[PDB]
Image: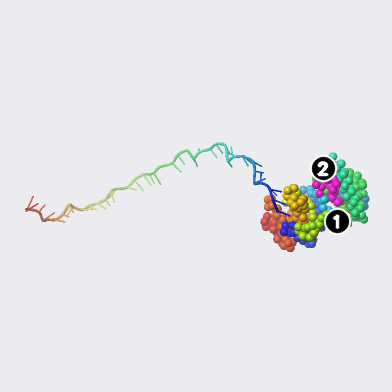
Amino acid sequence: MILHALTQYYQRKAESDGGIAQEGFENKEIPFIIVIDKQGNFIQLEDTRELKVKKKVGRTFLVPKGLGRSGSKSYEVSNLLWDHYGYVLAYAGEKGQEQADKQHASFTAKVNELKQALPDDAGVTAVAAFLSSAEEKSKVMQAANWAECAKVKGCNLSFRLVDEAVDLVCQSKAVREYVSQANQTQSDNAQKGICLVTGKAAPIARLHNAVKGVNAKPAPFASVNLSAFESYGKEQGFAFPIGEQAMFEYTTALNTLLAGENRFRIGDVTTVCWGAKRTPLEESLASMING
RNA sequence: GAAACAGGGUCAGCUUGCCGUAGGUGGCAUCGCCCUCGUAAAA
């Protein structure tokens, strides 16, 4: 009942003010956010990096998912608004600026289609004009704040537009409904059965969402990657069919648990710990008592 | 839901006195004493 249980807990977190990502997001940490007006052009640069024992990568913002780069044609894929410096600002960082430019090229296009698919939000218009006039930040990326010089702890920056100061353009309502309906449409495009978890016919998710914490590297919960494990011609990640919506559900539930206090990580075997009726008052304890 | 290695090896070694010494001693009557006796045996 592994995956089904994970899904149960995701449902609990969603329904119980747990503030988990809503089917359409990941709580990616933004090292710093560019504050913009209707034209941006470096209205301000806030650095969010101020955090715990180390100078971390910002405040936890349930921004759209990391669409993942996966190497070769990295620049083609670009996260929705929050993204890599070369994608967003076309900051050089190194000779890998040309690719960054291409990164920027697609990121712009992404933002541009974000404007085209979702107009009437000042944020996307703002970032579009921002991309047009990134020179205003071409100085700022060495004027206000820095990216720790290769691709580290300043990378994965994002955009916040002035006049709200607390809500990221990524997590802005308008952009949110866009990304949710987009996750719905692209899902509708793909095949439609069957969930291993909800058991309903639903979009099968290739590339399970790489839950983070058990391995040192964030790792797939279940990714039939190598060719042999590819069992019955389902051939990569359909080998296991799980509803992509439910894929999100459980992978986020697992991520939260793995990052929650419930991680009594005995040596290798990290051990999350649910409660079907969440908050059974033992869930928080179960690590403290076995660890 | 077939085919699938825990694997290919890895001195516990190297070496180290249980020793240097250390009275069983000093010493203490076997004693004090006691009839083999009373006796029957020259065929």
Q: CA distance from mark 2 to mark 1?
A: 38 Å
Q: Residue at x 90, y 54 (%)?
A: A117
Badge 1 marks a residue whose secondary structure is: helix
Amino acid type shown at disc 2: Cys
Badge 2 marks a residue whose secondary structure is: loop
Which region of the structure is painted magenta?
A68-93
- Magenta segment: does it hold A194? no
Q: Residue at x 84, y 48 (%)?
A: A77
Image position of A72 (left or right of A275) = right
Question: Which numbered disc, 2 or 1, marks the residue that appears first in the sequence?
Answer: 2
Labelled pair 2, 1 in contact (Cβ < 8 Å)? no
Q: Residue at x 82, y 52 (%)?
A: A65
Q: Which residue is mark 1?
A: A185
Amino acid type shown at disc 1: Thr
- Magenta segment: does it hold A71? yes
The lab-note entry on whether marks 2 and 1 share a chain reads yes
The reply to whether residue A85 is visible in this rendering is no
Q: Which residue is mark 2?
A: A149
In this orientation, which residue lies closer to the viewer: A12 or A236? A236
Q: Which mark is residue A65?
A: none
Chain on which label 2 sits: A
The reply to whether residue A230 is visible in this rendering is yes
